[PDB]
Image 1: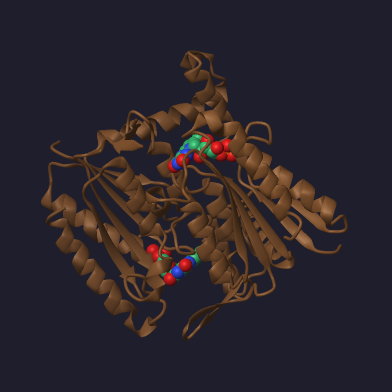
Image 2 (image 1 turned 90 degrees about the vertical axis):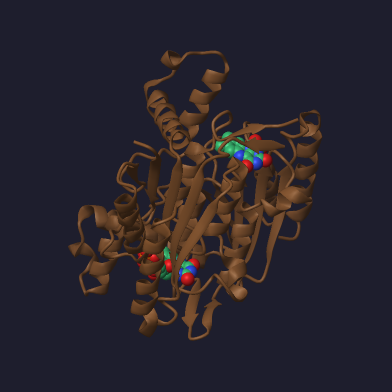
Length: 211
Length: 212
Ligand SMILES: Cc1cc2nc3c(=O)[nH]c(=O)nc-3n(C[C@H](O)[C@H](O)[C@H](O)COP(=O)(O)O)c2cc1C
Ligand SMILES: Cc1cc2nc3c(=O)[nH]c(=O)nc-3n(C[C@H](O)[C@H](O)[C@H](O)COP(=O)(O)O)c2cc1C
């Protein structure tokens, strides 16, 4: 139906155990409520196959750029290169992206990087210039991130690396709108944890009405 | 014996196909020449199992926090939890870290994140304080050899650099008083200078190896 949305989560736990998954689920449920015709796909990076770039991938790709045909690749190469192609094609096919992550050591879980590596593809999300130009000029994106401490303000802002990275990628891809929604401070101020969660949930629902 | 050095690589390919790995090899070979008694340990992130923190890990951890013995965890939980514990212990036990990576999409391969995740442990590499945190690796030092197609050491692309930037944040977090970089950069942007770029970086690696 009218827009395709990728709800992309990088968390091993669910909405009952995670600040990020709780806020993301509030967002996405509300979104669907408001845009009942839209195709909303949950991409759970912990459950799906998300191949890291490895020796097989490089081999396979080498092959393909040497004119060979997908048929010439080894089994394992086909499995991996193939999946990478599905992932990539699914990404460009969608209209909106919603990234949901916990902050682990100032950034996101490793699989989020695997996911990015799988979708950053010449001719699909960007193309090179006589630097590069992003092809995703009419997409839209949102990052929901949970963190123990505050990283929106203060000295600690300089250490934020998750959102920062995603912002860089979005820029690279030419996506003009990248929003952030943070559930921050629950670990630094645990008496405030319920309040922090509730307000983020409320912001998330509100944001869903417009995204 | 002597000093314990972790030579940490995040690459599927080897010294013959990789700029980072070639430069890293020059570095660490020289290091061992200069410091023959030092314990140089290759941590090959594409050969070791570096468990991502997953459902099994949270479960296993929670169990241990709940008083269960390690042997009471599931087979899977035990494998992952034990593996992470080893990685963590190994990191703190070492005196020096050498990170070698390619730049993929402005940062490093996913497994490098896994590795960091495995070694970032409260009471080991840092401690929480009512004021934030404090680093515990006050006697360590680190170097990062990074390879990239284009140039990230100036100007506008420098704001896009995220690999070295990340490792710098982590090292600061850990309280590591010294973290250096060595870049092999520009080889794709200016392929008619790739050989020279490489040769120069290799020379730098050999030089730097005399002090690290
Ligand atoms: C492995 C790990 C690493 C973490 N690293 C950080 C960090 O660098 N900064 C921070 O403020 N909080 C950190 N935390 C705390 C979490 O960010 C916090 O619990 C947040 O709610 C995580 O999201 P979740 O609740 O969706 O899991 C970390 C937690 C874990 C388990
Ligand atoms: C998956 C992938 C992603 C890459 N991303 C970037 C990038 O963001 N910026 C860049 O300058 N070069 C990029 N490159 C090119 C490499 O950084 C360059 O080839 C470098 O020499 C890689 O190190 P290596 O020779 O040790 O493998 C990328 C290459 C690959 C395979």
